[PDB]
Amino acid sequence: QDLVVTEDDCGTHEGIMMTPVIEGGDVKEPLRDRVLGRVTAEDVLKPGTADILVPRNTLLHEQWCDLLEENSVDAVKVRSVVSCDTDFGVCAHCYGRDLARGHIINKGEAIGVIAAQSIGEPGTQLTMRTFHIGGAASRAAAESSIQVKNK
Amino acid sequence: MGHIELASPTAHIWFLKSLPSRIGLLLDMPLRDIERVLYFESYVVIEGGMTNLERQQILTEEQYLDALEEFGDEFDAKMGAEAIQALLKSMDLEQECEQLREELNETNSETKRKKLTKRIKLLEAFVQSGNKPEWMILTVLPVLPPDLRPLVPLDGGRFATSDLNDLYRRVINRNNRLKRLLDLAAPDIIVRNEKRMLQEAVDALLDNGRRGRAITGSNKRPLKSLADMIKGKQGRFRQNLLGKRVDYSGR
Amino acid sequence: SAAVKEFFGSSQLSQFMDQNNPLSEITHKRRISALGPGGLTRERAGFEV
Amino acid sequence: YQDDELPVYQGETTQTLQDYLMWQVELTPFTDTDRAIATSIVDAVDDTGYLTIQIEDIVDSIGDDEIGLEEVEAVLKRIQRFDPVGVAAKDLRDCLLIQLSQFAKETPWLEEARLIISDHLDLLANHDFRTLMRVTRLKEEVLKEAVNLIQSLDXXXXXXXXXXXXXXXXXXXXXXXXXXXXXXXXXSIPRLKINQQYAAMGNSARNDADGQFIRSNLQEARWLIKSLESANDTLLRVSRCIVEQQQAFFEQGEEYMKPMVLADIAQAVEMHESTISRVTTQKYLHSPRGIXXXXXXXXXXXXXXXXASSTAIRALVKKLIAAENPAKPLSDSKLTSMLSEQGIMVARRTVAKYRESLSIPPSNQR
Amino acid sequence: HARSTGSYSLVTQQPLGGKAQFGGQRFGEMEVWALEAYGAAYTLQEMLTVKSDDVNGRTKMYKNIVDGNHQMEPGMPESFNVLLKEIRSLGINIELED
Amino acid sequence: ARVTVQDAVEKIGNRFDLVLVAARRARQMQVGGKDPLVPEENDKTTVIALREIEEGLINNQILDVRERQEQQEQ
Amino acid sequence: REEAVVWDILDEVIREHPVLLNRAPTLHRLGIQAFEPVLIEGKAIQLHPLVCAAYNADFDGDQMAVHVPLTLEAQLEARALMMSTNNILSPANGEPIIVPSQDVVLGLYYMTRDCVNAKGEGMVLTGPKEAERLYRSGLASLHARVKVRITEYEKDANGELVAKTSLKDTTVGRAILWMIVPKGLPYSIVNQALGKKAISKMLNTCYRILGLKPTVIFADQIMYTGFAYAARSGASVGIDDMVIPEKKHEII
Amino acid sequence: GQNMRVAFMPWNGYNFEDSILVSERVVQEDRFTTIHIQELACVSRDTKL
Amino acid sequence: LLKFLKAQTKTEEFDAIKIALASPDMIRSWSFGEVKKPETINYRTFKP
Amino acid sequence: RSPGVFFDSDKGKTHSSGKVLYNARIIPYRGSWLDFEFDPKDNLFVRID
Amino acid sequence: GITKASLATESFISAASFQETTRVLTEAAVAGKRDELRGLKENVIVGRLIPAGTGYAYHQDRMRRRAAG
DNA sequence: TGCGCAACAGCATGCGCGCCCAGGGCTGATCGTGCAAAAGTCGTGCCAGC
DNA sequence: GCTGGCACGACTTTTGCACTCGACTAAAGGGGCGCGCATGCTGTTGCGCA
RNA sequence: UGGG
């Protein structure tokens, strides 16, 4: 609860790498929903060298994120919280897009109540321990062969 | 507010149990030792610069009589709760502070720092706090205002008494017994028993849980003490901190 | 008279009968409860059982 | 659904509501000093709300520094209307004058008679009209609707009250008569004290600590049990012994009462007077008559050798003056002589005061 | 039910919870959490103090509503004072600063 | 009545401050000694304040010029 | 004494005065909101159906909690924040909420469909109206693969919308459904099966493009037409409704 | 309980989730009407006066 | 001696609540009197 | 539960080392209950009330 | 890991109702901590305005007086 | 080499555990002389008024 | 000359420091503290200087 | 005992 989110722009270059999860054969989450939002860190580069898509920080939405989906770039460097380093709060540009209203966050946000409670609203409908399903009851898989869905 | 005057010291049960204590390790003795010896029994000899026994010596009544015949003068031991007041009264804060500072500077280990670190930070923060060590034990005990313990007499049951009200008449009753029996010039066994009964009375008044857990005759139950009567559930939740019923609600 | 009148008068196995419908009376008279003097109170001992 | 021990909790009794006039003034649009003056007025309001102290005493007690009586007077008349049809103002006239102002403001023969009756001659017309009918100029029964309208006019206040404290005796001590003997059997007897000691005894071995606690938990508890059970048994035995001594010593069924020196009843058990007289203060007695173990211990020498104190005399004196005065004797000395004919040696001088006392109409009945 | 103004308890100066005897229902902790999630200070501020624990906020607030002023004028809760005294009974000292 | 406030906030975007500005204007019109610059729908002065903010002629600077002007003229 | 004038003055009081609603086990913040009351005759409270999904409750007769804001600034904090018309997107997923369900999905799903033959097949008429046939007689709701001329709107121009019309193949229910769609929404969104996945992203894009008010009143019109024509559908369930496969037995 | 003639459909969206709609005929026929009985007590006691 | 209100002066500005141990002298500074008897209220007198 | 002898395996999870512990409880109708238990030390132990 | 997080806060009034009150009141009573009333729950308990949202404005203004006297 | 020092393993004890909403019945307290001093009550006599 | 109000006087009642007194008593009473987890006391095991 |  203690985050007041007071300062607007801390002006730091630190960020976190953003890549798709790509777990196993079937990807769990695409790159669009992960890149969409927050604020771009440093720059991004198309496969053509010496070509910058965005001027340092930008507000990612359907236009810009769709332009990123139109290219082959697989990863985006994005600044976020715990990289803000600001004192007695969180910078407004470091944590962007609280959602709800479709514009940027302004001073006085609710922050960690929307955190927490946003996460705490689920958990009632969960199945908790999913043990004993073990599929067909066989132990792991004996075949070490590797296949592919596409080429 | 109001208050009461004991005429005898107590252990202030709100301390020394209370999660790892600020008392036992402050005097550098095992907690169980002080817990058993602080009232009504053992010796707890203090000072004794010319005596061969240690200042912290825990020696039982056997070595206490052995100290009466063998040692005599220069050996001063208080079997009551006043031994902590004198021994802690003679405690030097600065000499122990710099002594533990130089001891932690010269020698250090994996188990050394934790023992040293808790003690040194506690003593430094205690000196910078401004409070006196002897104030842990209470000479005067204040009483709750009358309205915070409403009787609420009922026509069926005449005057109703709260469960926590009887603690005051009990501690004042045993206190008047100890004071009336004190100046009477009686044997030491009876006055030691009185110090133990008053100790259990005050300790039961401040903290109901653990110890004697005194039970009512009619309604049984642990009843409630100041520790459980803070607010509600012994949180802030029930009568405060969004526990208020406001007005103009639903249904 | 105080023992038997106290047991029939006040107890956790002796309560008011539900007067609504005869079936609530019949299923109220026929019931099984793990509670009682030996008892299983609540909260505790509640999983496999 | 009984919830074990039940709520049994402090509960924070919500009743209060002795006087709401403070909450009434809190909503009055005063300026500055009118609020303080109003608080000074409402503090002097009696529980009955009829005649409250003196108007001059208020102003003298305000610490005026100017602020003349013309203001506080308008505050009086101002609050009296916002009051439940009225409060205070005393004089006994202002109550009925304000009650009739805003009530109706019309009917046959309301204000025409009400102004003169309320202004003057009221107390003269309270007993009976008679010649006053010639003073008011009214003819025969024209005033019947007027006085009849005043009857419904009515203590002015005491409408809210909300005093749940009815103060009941309940049980206490009881006595019974049977088989030719009206002897109390101490018909209370909760047995809780007896039961608790028996029940608490079970409790001492129930600590289940493993600490034994023989030194403090066991001996102290036992001592407390002996201390409370012995005290309750001694108090019940003393109350039963005094109830039997007063029972046997005097008989209620028999006409009249016998005076008992505090000493005779104290000399029966050979106990000091203070100990028993203190036990007879708050302890009552319930038999099949009336509704106190204090009025049955009245002591008096009756000022005569032939016979009983004053209770017998007082009841008898009211039973005498009850039916008497076929004409209009309005006489106390004649009752003292008739009482002296029985050998009671009544003074007949202080007799009237005793007779007059406790709601007796005498001697004002003349 | 729809309680407006009922009787008040002698302790903590709070209304009651029961119907017929006019309970004020309940306003809990998660509701304060939600009102903090909206970021409304005054909407919760009136419900924490004036509508519940303020003795003078009752009469003065109601007087301002009858006149149509609609002024808050917050006040100090009594339950916090109850906690104060309950701590003062213990050997622990707590005091306000000027 | 104004169902959507997004215009009046779209004037000067906060969505927190409209409560304070429309609150002060709501005190100016609510208490007394002032008149609305927009014709009334019979609605309460609250929606009048919201539509005055939606008109663009009431803001923090305007209230400062009116407050300092009426305070300096007296 | 509840005089008749007190009811009129009370009507003057309740008109724009907001009243906030909350449920007993509030988890997220949308569990408590602020709404405008309108007096109704009855002992219960009528709640908007689409907002019910935000409370995650159902109607078995559940009770509720109601609070009345006092003073002034509280009314501005209720009107500027807790109005459900003010905030739609929930601050968790980003996917919109209050999105219609239950009967609306049957009205829009039964609305959009086509079939072979039936009544009228295809025809040549002028749209978008097409209200002179189905709404009277001569055609069917989900029948015909009806070609009609329709005018679109394009927002690619800055600050201005350009109109474009053309003839397209569609169904009666879809062409009637296009009447509700304001302005610059593309026409390819209304031709689909509408499995609630179409209304989810349809209201999502509508809010993210045209803004708050047009998707609020647009979703409202979707509600009214959804329960209206959902009631026009008249579906039912029965014993013959369920069919057991003939092979199943053998497999067992 | 009492039998009724059930029809299964939505009617102008008035049925939502588990709710139900009733005709006025059920009200006019007096069906689904109950009677309650409440006990009132007043005590007269002998006080100190 | 007139126009005095103790409710208006009961509200003051306060910030940064502190917690500290108590001393017997400061406890006596709060002491308005002493209770010398365990008894509470008399049943016959109905007064403390 | 009826009074008598109960042989219980306790589920064999106590010290986490995966050792089975078989205990038993003789419970009369009234009076003190008698219990026999095994510790991981492989020695017999008795718990009385 | 959130088990010591609320217990290690620099304000003794907050989180005291979240966990055991004994150790918090003993360590705070001996240490002499000052709360400064910078937490949300503390302003909710005391009754002062919340330093967030619409209140964050007001609490900002008074803030510039703090260091300025 | 054996004793000496330090570390690790086992046993005990303490703290905890969702919200809201409604009805019904009762339920610890008080000990108990003697002596002395104070206050109240009751009775008688005197004065005042009719 | 008679009636009613008031004054004086006892004796009669009200009141305040004081201690008293030891019981005893065995039966009853609770059991299963659902649980999990973290922190501290101690005893035994392993490893080094000399 | 019962309702979400």
Image: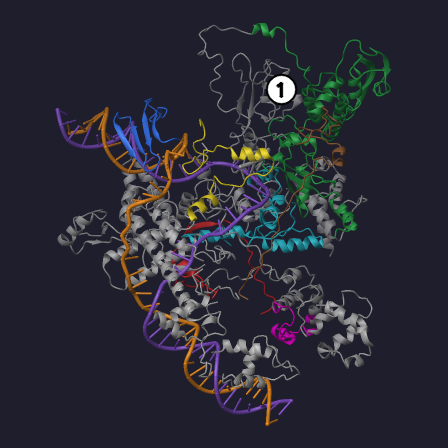
Chain colours: C yellow, E cyan, G green, H brown, I red, J blue, L purple, M orange
Q: Is residue E90 visible?
A: yes
Residue of label 1: A53
Element marked by disc 1: loop
Q: Amino acid at mark 1?
A: Leu
Residue positioned most to the front: D179
Residue A133 image offset from top left, x and y in percent: 49, 17
Q: Quadrant of the N terminus of chain B?
A: bottom left
* Magenta: main secondary structure: loop
The correct choice, above or below, for B86 with respect to E2 in the image is below
Q: Residue at x 36, y 59 (%)?
A: D233
Residue D256 image offset from top left, x and y in percent: 49, 74
- G198 vs B222, left or right, is right
Q: Residue at x 70, y 22 (%)?
A: G105
Residue H43 image offset from top left, x and y in percent: 58, 56
Residue J45 in magenta stretch: no
Q: Residue at x 37, y 62 (%)?
A: D237
- D53 vs D149, left or right, is left
Looking at the picture, tell me which residue is in the foreground, E95 or J5. J5
Boundaries of the magenta span: D44-72
